Image 1: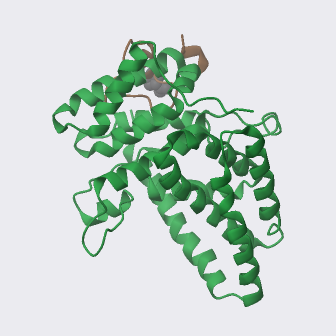
Image 2 (image 1 turned 120 degrees about the horizontal axis):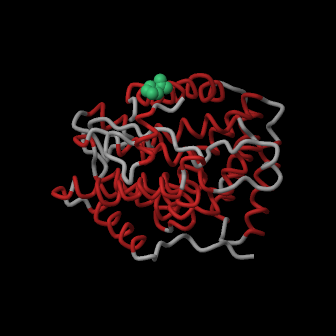
Image 3 (image 1 turned 90 degrees about the vertical axis):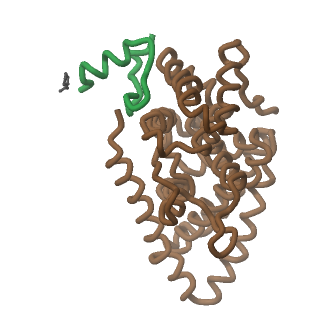
Length: 296
Length: 31
Ligand code: PRO
């Protein structure tokens, strides 16, 4: 069972943290001196292109890791600049998941590897990153509320198309799927050899169990197409490794989301539910896919 | 610390909506 008061408390903890990020970091930098703002502008735009330069190549991954670490280290003495840049990185990584991973899901693999590396090299990033994930995509911790009211829409990460028109369903769903794709990857990657003996994985595979369990425990009147979308994005990114981790228990939970949850919502004809059932069927036919291994 | 009811659920051949254990099973409960 799931205690939804504690998940709600966890949601509003990260929502309070987003608010704390704005007051204690963003405005200080807005009210700050010019020579430092220019340096951070030079650094801000020297950093942003790196995420797009990732490819399916490990050699290229290691290059981008190194170059981002040198740029973050340029601020390590300066707490306000250091936390401002990590907040920026956390935003840029989520934005990449919302945009590039959306159109090319397999690009979540290199990006997740890069993010996991940054999360252990610079562990102040963990709370900044998780706060940004929860605010923009509350499915990452299994939070769900009604989206009939304007306040509920906002909590669940919806944007405005204009004044009093919500962003279209496809836009929202594909953004959520891309973000969750990235997080899914991270939970099923192992730490690099440089950290794995010394450091706990900061976002381990247990967190994928939480997502599936909590959605399966969510009152069905709150389930929407987006739950099925993010579960399918999750599946393409991590189902193979989830089965490796939890075996028969993973299998029971995959059956629960792919057969039972889709069946119970069948009359809604959610496009995401149809795709999740197709993924279940591929697994049942010993044809489960995973993203191709990265090349040399 | 795992309740007997949770152990029973992990022993079963299925989970049910609303009753999935929030915390993943330890290795001892994976076949
Ligand atoms: O740990 C406990 O207290 C649960 C209660 C039922 C049996 N075991």
